[PDB]
Length: 128
Length: 128
Ligand code: NI
Ligand code: NI
Image (tube, rainbow over all chains, first blue to last red; front, side, top):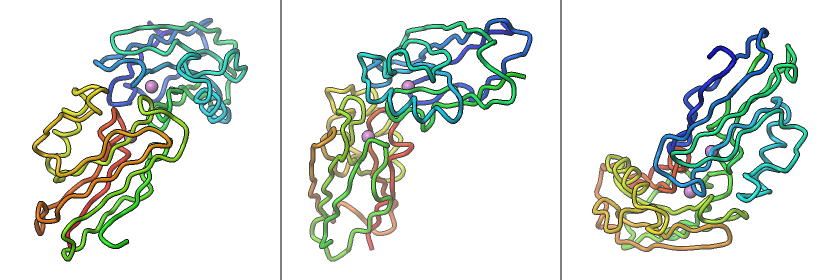
């Protein structure tokens, strides 16, 4: 609870929220991702990727180009603050990261890098 | 141009038009679908499927449930007036159907049934 949050990304190409705020008291923060649905990861794969608003675009465009083998994320991309695995239906994955990696007054974005999904599957994250 | 429309499906999950006018003087109308870009069928597949605005949702839902091998279309869906195959990048397909299958004052939709795309890839077709 509190320094964790649960996200689901479904077969309708959406996330159950478009805003997460990290509380300034958290030492670490967890994002638990699940995929309700029936569709396979090769058609409707979802991951949770975090970065700044200004970088999102770069991360999606190089993610795309990497492909399904690299879970559509450029390996060791330094713009990526934290990311889960690309999961399909019935799969579950989570990531914990240092709240120290986030600074106040900066717009972060959570999104999915599977092609075309960030048009809908995106959200703001903010450290309050 | 004359009783036919050239249309494009791109890797941004966008068709290059969102309104088709079919002329009453046509015996037939031909739609010519192409897919500029680089992503394959299993990731950014596109088809042009036509039905009444009312049947669209049943076609989209059942299409999803038909699977990738079925080109995400319920085969012999009684509601589909015409459709192309689901094409990936570099590919192309056309469909010619008779104009008598359309009537005056019905609302028709064209759309793509690939998972999550029709919220974005959709337009109106109209008999004038
Ligand atoms: Ni996704
Ligand atoms: Ni499509």
